[PDB]
Image (cartoon, rainbow, N blue to C red; front, side):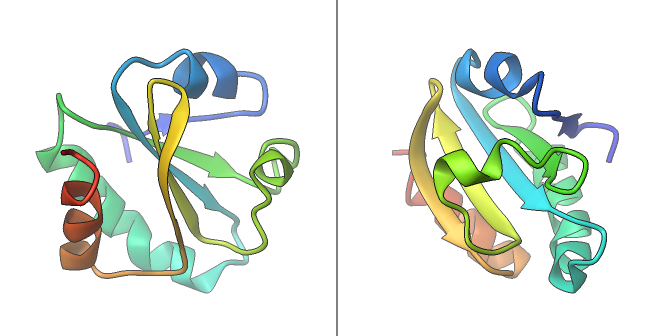
Length: 108
């Protein structure tokens, strides 16, 4: 949880849209049960993908402003950004293996 950038509505443009390369963003809240499943999964991915992928987190309760701009209907939603632009999205939980697949499908 230390390698993950903690985003706010205020920082999101700088840490995501101004960000060079690839950023995995996780939209989550404290009441979301399956957000707790993928949190440790996201910690391990940040661990292993360190240097070719940044993992970042956004709490939608503390930061209500960003998720509507991407028409996010449910959490957890993962958005993979490349050079401030959406490369891919994933709505719902997944396993660690599945997330690696997801990333390979996009890391050309």
